[PDB]
Amino acid sequence: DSTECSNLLLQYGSFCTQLNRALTGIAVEQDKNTQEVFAQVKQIYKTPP
Amino acid sequence: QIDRLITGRLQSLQTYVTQQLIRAAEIRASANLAATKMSECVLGQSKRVD
Image (cartoon, rainbow over all chains, first blue to last red; front, side, top):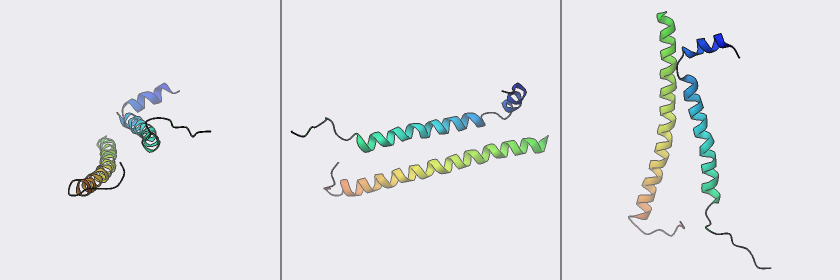
């Protein structure tokens, strides 16, 4: 919420772009981790009564 | 003016090099896994499930 500051920031380039990219990469890697660890069974078995 | 430009470009280069370092480490981990898999799974038969 400061237009002049945003104008100044535009001069630095793509620093903030690199940061958002990196954090998105981490955020998807987390779900990759949990699926790989747990999703190893094809079906859902159930013990008999 | 020249000093300010130098500082900006230097920060950009720092960021790129650090990013490269981290990515190279992850690639090395994957390559070690590949070497272990090849040695234990081609040059012989393995009994480790999946």
